[PDB]
Amino acid sequence: XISXXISXALI
Amino acid sequence: XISXXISXALI
Amino acid sequence: XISXXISXALI
Amino acid sequence: XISXXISXALI
Image (cartoon, helix red, strand yellow):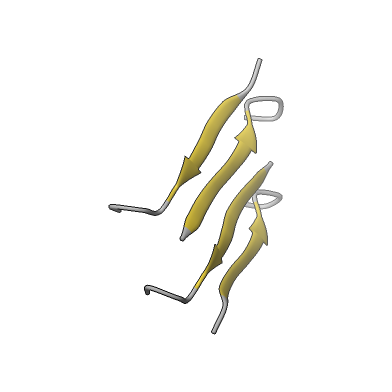
């Protein structure tokens, strides 16, 4: 259904 | 900072 | 569908 | 100021 999310802290 | 998003319809 | 985001503060 | 945007359509 849904895939991904939120990042950019570390990488 | 923020990278990614939301997917899973077409793909 | 949607991927990327907002940056250029930290990196 | 800001960098990135919206992708994940063709790629």
